[PDB]
Amino acid sequence: TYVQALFDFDPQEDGELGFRRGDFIHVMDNSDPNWWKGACHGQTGMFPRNYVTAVN
Amino acid sequence: IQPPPVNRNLKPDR
């Protein structure tokens, strides 16, 4: 399950996943409707659902 | 085009 970043996300709190617009993120736990958890650049962390889009 | 507001009170670690 993959998504792609719609915007840069600059993390502010421990647990927040940093990424740039266009990056692909591997979704690991999307149980929360608001904040998904996944992996990018060799880290796990959480980020808002609405900062990404699902991809194929 | 603008990034959405980030809603940290909704974070699942809270």
Image (spheres, coloured by chain):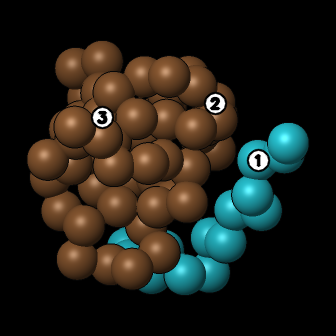
Chain colours: A brown, B cyan
- The chain ID associated with circle 2 is A
The chain letter for the residue carrying disc 1 is: B
Residue type at the position of mark 2: Asp
Residue with the mark numbered 2: A8
Q: Residues within 10 Å of mark 2 (few under 14, many from 20)?
A: some
Question: Along the line of sight, which residue is nearer the eye, B9 or A32?
Answer: A32
Give percent across and percent down for residue B7.
67, 72
Residue located at (21% from left, 48% from top) = A27
Q: Position of residue A17 (x, y in %)?
A: 43, 39
| Residues under numbered marks 2 and 1 in contact, where contact means CB atoms less than 8 Å apart | yes
With A47 as the anchor, is A38 left or right in this view? left
**Which of marks 3 and 2 precedes in the sequence?**
2
Please provide percent x and percent y for residue A15.
Answer: 40, 49
**Figure check: A30 above or below A54:** below
Q: Residues within 10 Å of mark 1 (few under 14, many from 20)?
A: few
As measured in the structure, the alpha-carbon distance from the residue carrying label 3 to the one carrying label 1 is 17 Å
Q: Residue lying furthest top in this view?
A: A41
- Residue nearest the viewer, comparing B5 with A45: B5
Q: Nearer the viewer, residue A21 or A29?
A: A21
> CA–CA distance between discs 2 and 3?
12 Å
Counting the numbered discs, the total is 3
Residue type highlighted by circle 3 = Ile
Please give the residue where the numbered disc 1 appears in the rendered image: B3
Answer above or below: position of A25 versus B8: above
Q: Quadrant of the C terminus of chain A?
A: top left
User: Label 3 is found on which chain of the structure?
Assistant: A
Q: Is residue B6 left or right of residue A53?
A: right
Image quadrant assignment for residue A36:
bottom left
Q: Which residue is mark 3?
A: A25
| Identity of the residue drawn at 55% across and 60% down | A50
Question: Mark 1 falls on what kind of element?
Answer: loop
